[PDB]
Image (tube, helix red, strand yellow):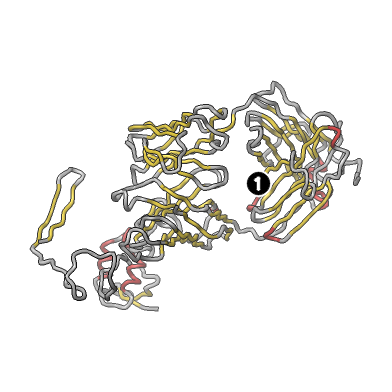
Amino acid sequence: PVMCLLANTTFPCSQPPCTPCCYEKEPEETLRMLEDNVMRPGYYQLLQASLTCSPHRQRR
Amino acid sequence: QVQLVQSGAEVKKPGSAVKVSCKASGGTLRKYAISWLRQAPGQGLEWMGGIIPIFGTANYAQKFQGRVTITADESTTTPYTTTPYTSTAYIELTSLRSEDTAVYYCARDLGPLTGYSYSYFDYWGQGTLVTVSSASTKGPSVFPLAPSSKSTSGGTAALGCLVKDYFPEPVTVSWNSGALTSGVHTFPAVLQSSGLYSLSSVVTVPSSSLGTQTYICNVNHKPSNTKVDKKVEPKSCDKTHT
Amino acid sequence: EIVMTQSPATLSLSPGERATLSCRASQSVSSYLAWYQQKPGQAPRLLIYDASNRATGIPDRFSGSGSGTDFTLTISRLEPEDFAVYYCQQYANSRRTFGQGTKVEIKRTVAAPSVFIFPPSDEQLKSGTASVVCLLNNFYPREAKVQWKVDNALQSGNSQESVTEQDSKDSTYSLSSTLTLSKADYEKHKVYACEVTHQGLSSPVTKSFNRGE
Amino acid sequence: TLTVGFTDGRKISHSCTHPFHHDPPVIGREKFHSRPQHGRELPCSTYAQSTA
């Protein structure tokens, strides 16, 4: 799969290290992650894993 | 005038998914939402959300926004204010659970043109039944009922028959092989353990009509191609066939 | 949250009477409220599109009224095709809330149920099972009661229930329950009965049978 | 000039007004003012309605 960097940790963009519900738990960790990922071919996949369609309240 | 048509009624395993499909046709307007509702198999009537198909925009009830995706086929052609228009819409129910068993409606919704506002629901689809269990397709168990050690006489008399262990509800059940439909009664459905169906069927008559005709009950079940025609005579101790 | 409520859960009326279905909401919704009809097994039908305003194709029998928390649907000369379920719905808030649903049913004089009980047939017992079935039949109002006697003691945590809806000719109604056992407990228990009660009965019209007789 | 605005729940209203030279290019060879109920089709471009 496509890979991206948090800080010291590299990860698969289908299952980033924050998962689940990254922006519900930790907006600033999401900021600190995304600041270096603004320029990768997985950026939108990481958005889809961290805060868009990924967060929920009802069990899926 | 306008109509909504929605296609297929279903049973599926828990943890699998469905996409109930709608088509809207024949209206004069061009900006309606198509909005999704469920009617619970006991009681209740639930708001799910809607889409505006010209925009593809979607929004949800706060009790569904985790589970389901509403979506549509995009856009509209014209400002002409009288020529034809049609739209299609969907609910993607991911990860099915027991209580997702319901009748689902699409409906035409004027929220995007009553100004911009919330709305009543003006025209409704066919209503599609969806059901959830880990059970499997099977044909019915088909047992007769009969008289037992009692006076077997006076007032109303009846014999009856029972159906159980079938999956999906469309059994067809009838009496006398297509005759004398007066005095027929049925208890149409109940669910046995793990979601297998059961039905009770009867004919009721005056006392002297009990021992005096060929009582025959007819059972067929389309989901399993099962067919059964048989009599319902006394079977407790006075073992009878005519 | 807006709680929506309807005054009777069900009501019964003669054809040609005047119905007065009535609704209450928690805190004012202030118009933005609809009413609907549902013929049995069919999709719903709109009656009124706001609290005073009648929908298209509504044949003048019907009217709406309401303000703040309080709303009503009136049907004048209730016809034999107007017997259906009826719902309010508010659209004053982002949670679009339907009311609980009220059935309107064909009024009748009281009639007591005639009674039946039936054994297992041999195929159940060769399959390792037994079921005992009863009827409380052709009666009114829709309001009878059933429970199970085994060795003349009460036991009923096994049992199912079902009903036949109102006769379209007659309004009259019907009720059934099934008791069920494995073959071993059916051979143990020697007598079976269904206990009977109704609004038009002072005492059970009980019927009974013995196992295998 | 182009101005856009709205209203609070408070009934207070707001607007913002820019200078802006709005004048659509001509399509075809006739400087018409509203779409006609008879005519011909010519190719052009449009911000499409989809929120995708």
- Which residue shows up at 73% across the image and 36% down it? C135
Q: Is residue B30 above or below residue C29?
A: below
Image quadrant where one finds the C terminus of chain B = top right
Of residues B68 and C23, the one drawn nearer to the viewer in this rendering: C23
Q: Residue at x 29, y 73 (%)?
A: D41
Residue that protrudes farthest toward the front in the picture? D38
Q: Looking at the rendering, which quadrant does residue A46 occupy?
A: bottom left
Label 1 crowd bin: few (<14), some (14–19), many (20+), radius 10 Å: some
Label 1: which residue?
B189
Is residue B209 something one can see in this rendering? Answer: yes
List the single residue furthest toward the left.
D19
Q: Position of residue C187 (x, y in %)?
A: 83, 43
Identity of the residue drawn at 34% across and 60% down: B57
Quarter location, residue B206: top right
Residue C84 position in % (x across, y down)? 54, 38
- As shown in the figure, which amino acid type bears the numbered disc 1? Ala
Is residue C147 found left or right of B212 in the rendered image? Answer: left
